[PDB]
Amino acid sequence: MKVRPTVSSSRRKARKAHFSAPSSVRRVIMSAPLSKELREKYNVRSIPIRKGDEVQIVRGAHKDKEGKVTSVYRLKYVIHVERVTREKATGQTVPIGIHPSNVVITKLHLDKDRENILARIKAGREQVAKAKG
Amino acid sequence: NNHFRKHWQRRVRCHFDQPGKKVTRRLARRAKAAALAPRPVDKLRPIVRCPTVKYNRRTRLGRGFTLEELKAAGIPRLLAPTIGIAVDHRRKNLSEESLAANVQRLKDYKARLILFPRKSNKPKKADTPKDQQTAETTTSLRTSFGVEQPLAPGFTEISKSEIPAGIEGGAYRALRKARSDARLVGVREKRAKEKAEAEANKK
Amino acid sequence: SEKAGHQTSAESWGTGRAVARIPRVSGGGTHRAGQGAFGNMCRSGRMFAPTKIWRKWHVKINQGQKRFATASALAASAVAPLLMARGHQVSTVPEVPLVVDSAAVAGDAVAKTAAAYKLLKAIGAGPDVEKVKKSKKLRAGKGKMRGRRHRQRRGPLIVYSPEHDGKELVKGFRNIPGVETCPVDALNLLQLAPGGHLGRFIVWTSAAIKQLDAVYESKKGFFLPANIVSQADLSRLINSTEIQSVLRAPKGEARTKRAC
RNA sequence: AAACUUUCAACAACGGAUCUCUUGGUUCUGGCAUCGAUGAAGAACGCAGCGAAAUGCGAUAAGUAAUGUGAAUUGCAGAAUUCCGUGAAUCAUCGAAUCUUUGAACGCACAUUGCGCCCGCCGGUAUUCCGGCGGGCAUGCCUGUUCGAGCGUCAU
RNA sequence: CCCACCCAUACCCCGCCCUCAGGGUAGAAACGAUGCCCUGAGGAGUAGGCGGCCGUGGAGGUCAGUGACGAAGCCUAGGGCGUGAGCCCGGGUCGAACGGCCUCUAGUGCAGAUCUUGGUGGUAGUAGCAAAUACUUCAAUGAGAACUUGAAGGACCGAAGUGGGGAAAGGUUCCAUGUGAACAGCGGUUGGACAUGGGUUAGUCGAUCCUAAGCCAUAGGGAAGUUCCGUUUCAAAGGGGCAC
RNA sequence: CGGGACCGAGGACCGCGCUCUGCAAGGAUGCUGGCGUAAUGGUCACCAGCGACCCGUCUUGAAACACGGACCAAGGAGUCAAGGUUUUGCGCGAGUGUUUGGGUGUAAAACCCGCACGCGUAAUGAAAGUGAACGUAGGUGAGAGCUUCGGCGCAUCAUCGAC
RNA sequence: AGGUUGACCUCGGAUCAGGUAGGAGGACCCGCUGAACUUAAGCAUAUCAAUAAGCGGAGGAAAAGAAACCAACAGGGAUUGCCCUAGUAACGGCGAGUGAAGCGGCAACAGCUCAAAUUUGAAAGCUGGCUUCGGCCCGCGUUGUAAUUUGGAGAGGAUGCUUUGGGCGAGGCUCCUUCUGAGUUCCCUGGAACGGGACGCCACAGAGGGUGAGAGCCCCGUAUAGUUGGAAGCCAAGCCUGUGUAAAGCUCCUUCGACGAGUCGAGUAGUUUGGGAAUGCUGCUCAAAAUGGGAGGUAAAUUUCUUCUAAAGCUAAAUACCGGCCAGAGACCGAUAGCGCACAAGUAGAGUGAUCGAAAGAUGAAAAGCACUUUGAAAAGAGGGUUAAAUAGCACGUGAAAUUGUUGAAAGGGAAGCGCUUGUGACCAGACUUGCGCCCGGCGGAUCAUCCGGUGUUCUCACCGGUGCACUCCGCCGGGCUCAGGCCAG
């Protein structure tokens, strides 16, 4: 149950905010879980997905397919994974849209901003666990 | 007896904001108490008697103490509103009893007052010393200095030998005589004046 | 809105040979022109007797009758058949009314939801809690769009003493579905008789069961009501010796033979 | 007998009811006090590689700066990002700016892209001519300045 | 005058429904006692009055309710229950929710209002598509040519024109190329239609300047005021020259 | 003493009786045959015999006249508030009413508090004003119920008294 | 030089130096102006209504406000608002109707500034300019700018005690920022689990939303304490210092003690009010006073009494809010509803103009929006794929009725439709299929009766373990027999 007066449990307002969120909010909305190995390595459960990450699909008809993320279509709330495609009528290849909450990240695309994100998320997690313990 | 012949629907006031306004008033009271601490949230009020013959049986809280009451209590009129005492310059003391009651009220408040110095490092002799500054305090003068006995006691007991004899002739006859004398005060004065004039003329 | 149906310019075309005398939107060049207006039978008109905010939404109830109903609901909560008739799973409850020791709830003993859930399972409210957990369904109707999306049954009501037991048990019991808490000095009829049906399953603390008598002593202007019946056992009254010894002999039986 | 008209049924039409949905209304409650000559509200005209509108913006024109985030945008085209970075983005924030013609609207006018006046600067042979650019020129009233008028009251 | 016969929802007997009335039913082996058993009478109905039930949207409680192994809705010469409003089931279609019971609540039940909005018939392939004299041949284009083009003919406007240019008004209709549908009350390869581009060059032509009838500022006076009068006034309303 | 038609309500026994091993006496049993499925039954369409004006609406006493209706779907008209009044249910009762407000809260809920006030507890008069027991709160006649069987007598009605 | 040279006063000029107003908004607020429909049978008093429209002016509130008050009491004590007073006092053709206030309870409370005095041993005051920020100048002003005093008083005396100025400041609060628990474990259905089943886990978090169907644990968020970094304010425990040149308070007193004029008031006229004997406002005429003046809800004279102190001014809160901005909600509506507008809606369109003003949402989870072949000039058609489904084809969820086409059946000599009852044809729901009980025979087992112990009960009834040793119980299979069984009939 929500307590704070600034929190709204309105379905209409929640759906309006979700479907009219700007791009920087949609990045956080399109977050994906890490694999077990990455979670035990970084002490991080979830991260916003980005181009260049390697993912494995764990839901839908393309389950157990792995590949690099080639596009983050934030306008459609969907990602594109390499070789997870279909043929059109003509036989040309078109990517199949996968929601990021249906995949798990197996190899992070690592740069210093990403290490800063992982480090501050991890440090907050251990600080919260230590304070509550 | 239905007064609905004007455009009454334009001036309908509903009160759906009654709990919200109570919450707002309580929040304002909490803010005022926090801003005024450790002083009480209200000012000290005197005891007055309600006017008219309907309500003069009952006493209540008045606006402020009189200048005569402050003088008899020894509290200067410029110091009084700065230590939580309300002052009313319009009210006068026509009788000694209310004056004595309010003076005793001011003296009790002065005996219970803790006055902090303006500068902590330089206390004055009118100020409360630091060893006496710590005590259990009150924050509602309307509660701690309310109207204790608003009406007279409705029942007492006396010995049977202390029963009064009563007014001669009876209370009903006394009331009738008082009304008759009040109605005939002018006629008897005119008759006495005419009789005195006749006696002076034919002495 | 008070202006709905009336933000239009329209006038009747009068008695004639062709059309009805409803006012019609003036002007031209659009579909609205010449169409009926202002009528409760008209499309985009004003509704009949428009709803007003000065309807009587609230009901004033006598405080004595409120206290009577609360006392009746508390008395009904001590009758084990009424709990089953109201639908509580109380077959494993060791005693009704169920009183738990205040040492098991006071302080921070059940400040954690796991501890509160374990305590409920150990004292026997477990089947009622799981009944609530399994009873969750999607509501039929427009309440889903209006923010009342799910329905579920009511579970046990925990009554405690805030002075002796503290208030962390409220946080401990908060997240369990169907479980409600209430201070012993602020008992709510809307919880004691949900839906107007008597027999709510109540878990008491020992401090609350100690404080209940003082709670009902402190209600000024109210006394516990005297009943119009002293002995509720109608069978005992009717089959007592005192009544049966003065009765007339039976004039017939439960079934009558047909004479002709 | 068929055709025709009507009745009943199945499928197909016509039409958009019913059901389910809702980034919208409606009502209530709570919080806040902030437009404009330092040019508002409103109006017109423009601005994207590929837009008519809606949206955003003003010749710095679907935007500039700054701060934050940290890899997009996407309908097509074209380019990215040294990804171990002064950094993508139709991102968020927003304290620095730009802000056409107007409008209380202010040189005079305006059914005209009409006609002026003052002061500087630049260019074309240029003391005279031509052109461009910049800053100004409304009214009522207040305070002060300075220049005045009148046997209105006086002194000398 | 006589005999027989025919049939009303009337009368007689019997069954069933409902209403009313009168009885029975606890040391309860005892009951939706708001039930059950026994007996009798009665049955039209407008205005009007009262009672009980059915149905719809929403709310509390409850049914450990139904549901992608198919909710709701819809169709049904398929059935069951109810005097009835209705309720339930089967078959088909369909795709995400919905229902029973007790209370609560209302924007709660349609054949009519020359209603309201939307949709659809017969009339009916009907009434017409008949003012302005009129069209024809060959070739080309094209899927297709009376109403496209070229040539060949025949006619009309007949200089107060069916001609050549302008003012008002319109605003790209102008020109070239291309074109499915729609529009051109037929037809269309054509078009003022649709699509993409292009086109308007001034010291001398107009505007711009002047004043006309007239209109608006200023001074000043009215008016609560929006504002009204006033346009030469009861205004200090400015130009020029000379100077040891 | 024959001939025919329609019907069989009820569901252990109990009763009135008789022609009394039993019965025709407070309501149908016994025996037999075919079939066991569309045969009975039902629904729909049609033919046949008989029956049968087009619905509101208005008018007056009534008809007729008149007015509305091409068809279908969806809306579509005795509602809400205040103040009375009678009746029903409920709480308390010579009192009653927490909610203007305050306290409190799991926060428009629920729970709690009290001064004043409203209505009631007294009326009458224009007003000044005055203000309800002779009596077991009276007598008489009825009156449900109770009774120790002499009476006591509810509510209520009629009548005479008292304040 | 005096026919000059000046000082003032009033009135002007300047694109002089520096400023200010206009318009928008107007829900609420302060005024002005001001109807009629309506209701009174009609209708000039009246009512609607001191309302709508029109005009001027403000703010986050506005306005009101510290008594020329209420009262008649044992007196209350600025203003505002709620409850009550109270549908009361009172007003009212031919009556329809209208209608306050004091007290009382509460919310909130907060008090003050001038004019009338000589600083007169010192205009002690102030705008502007230039500044080296030390001041210096041009001026305003004595026709009065500071100090002092405001009726509660004060001034003058007397008298002896008290009072004060600066600077740090721990700490706390407000607002943005970093960060927060737990399954994508196994099976089945399914195109897709977010469904069903099993095993777990988190919970101060089981609010809400998203994700290919109902997700606490896939994702965003949700709960709670805190925890990174930053800015500006406010409150505040205390701590350092200067001290009395000066200002201030208290107590007493012979005395003094200025207090707002075309105003108050009166008459008259209009309007207004419950104040049509007692109200307010405005216009015209008259026009004050010094224990004076106002009020004391019936006119006047006389004598008293009681209350205040007008004709100058400021001020937070409690109160209002169909405007604006931000936010949270609902027993509200669900695309003919709800705002006119869920959509490029105050749009398209119409009107010279003021203004008037719509219609219109939904493929699918994902465009996967049909490759390729073939017929056609094309639109399209047919095959063949795509999809879970094209019985979803950008005419797109579902797809009712009116009305239409085809197919099948039937009827029809100037209407059809409907009621009762057969018949024919077509199409159907039930019912039935065997049950129970005895007598034999064959199997397969001992939860037959009795007794013993334990346990529970309704305290005499049961359950569990041992004993059965097969003429006793329990099932099954073959025969036989009685009874009861469906439809129509004699």
Image (cartoon, coloured by chain):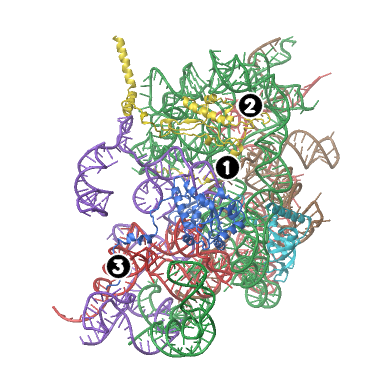
Chain colours: A cyan, B yellow, C blue, D brown, E red, F purple, G green
Residue at the image position 72 percent from the left and 58 percent from the top: A44
Q: CA distance from mark 3 to mark 1?
A: 76 Å
What residue sits 45% from the left and 48% below the top? C63
Quadrant in the picture for residue C133? bottom right
Q: Amino acid at mark 3?
A: Gly
Compared across the picture, whether F119 is left or right of D155 comes to left
- What number is the disc on residue B27? 1
On the same chain, marks 2 and 3? The answer is: no
- Host chain of mark 1: B
Left or right, residue F62 beside residue G188: left
Residue A125 visible? The answer is yes
User: With respect to residue G5, does B165 lie above or below?
Assistant: below
**The one of F21 and C153 positioned closer to us in this rendering:** F21
Chain bearing mark 3: C
Q: Element under label 2?
A: loop
Camera-nearest residue between G184 and G176: G184
Q: CA distance from mark 2 to mark 1?
A: 38 Å
Residue hosting label 3? C252
